[PDB]
Image 1: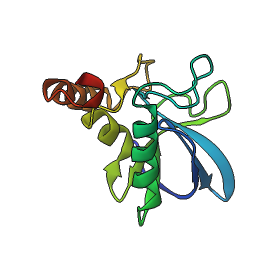
Image 2 (image 1 turned 90 degrees about the vertical axis):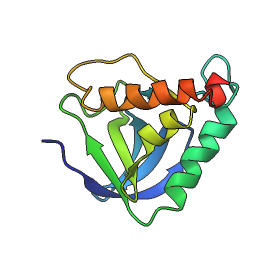
Image 3 (image 1 turned 30 degrees about the horizontal axis):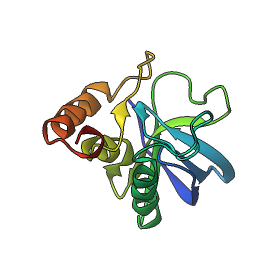
Length: 136
């Protein structure tokens, strides 16, 4: 069973990355299973909808009363030392909110870190259908 754990917002970095205080230590978290347009793309810099996705995540985390992180079944940190997790702001999963709003696509999946894959694909299908942002 996956379980949620409290964290405290330090700073929103980009649409897909947020720095949190987890277990008393500052850490950078990469949102699992989603690829958002970035403002800090290593090769492109600011992408189309990058500023929008970035503001959406920032707003969501900054205005939350409670932030919780939920690790999946596999590796919990990537190659760059970023925690890999599903982030919740007042019970709402930020990863899903972005996809539902057409501000992110479901990323290439690496088992066993795919617990919420179907949920996200479902939201992405709806966003595509509604021709939202990325899909307009």
